[PDB]
Image (tube, rainbow, N blue to C red; front, side, top):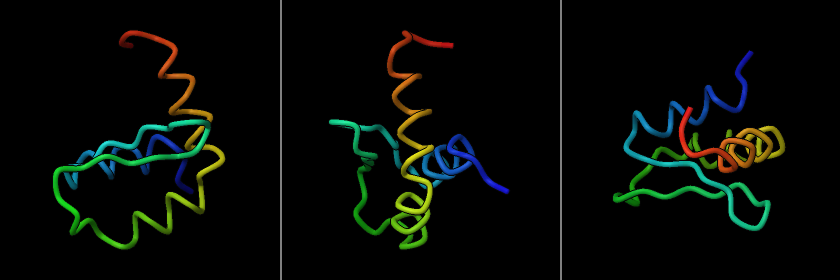
Length: 62
């Protein structure tokens, strides 16, 4: 059973960076040929992804 951080790490491995903007789960990358699985899992767990990606956005580093 995955969680927000699981998918976040998967993004980094593929050379992507999940970050939320306006409480909407966003993604950043240098390549557009990202795996389509990310677009779906990101939307599947967008709620928890936001929660985790936004609470981390509040701190400098951890």
